[PDB]
Length: 29
Image (cartoon, rainbow, N blue to C red; front, side, top):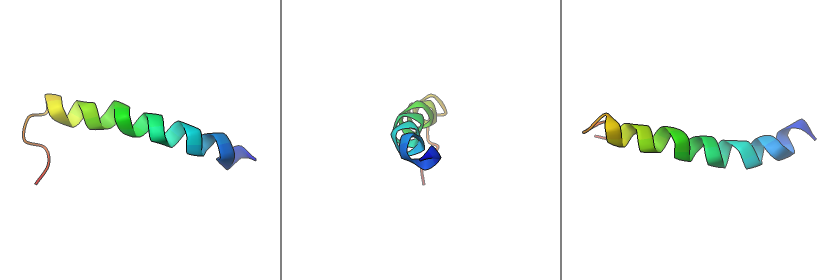
């Protein structure tokens, strides 16, 4: 289904954004 590979997508996308918070410095409170 469309959301089957989205589930494969999101997990990667998460990594892409979560590494970006790092570059934002103290972006997690």
